[PDB]
Amino acid sequence: IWGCXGKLICTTA
Image (tube, rainbow, N blue to C red):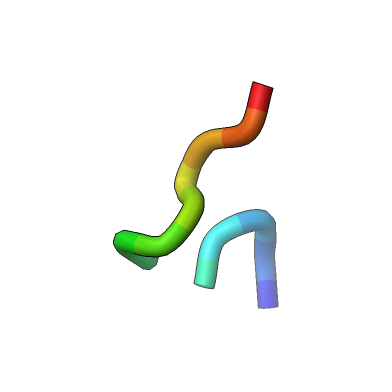
């Protein structure tokens, strides 16, 4: 349960 759960949204800026 971190910023990323994988190839979904491993980036947001």
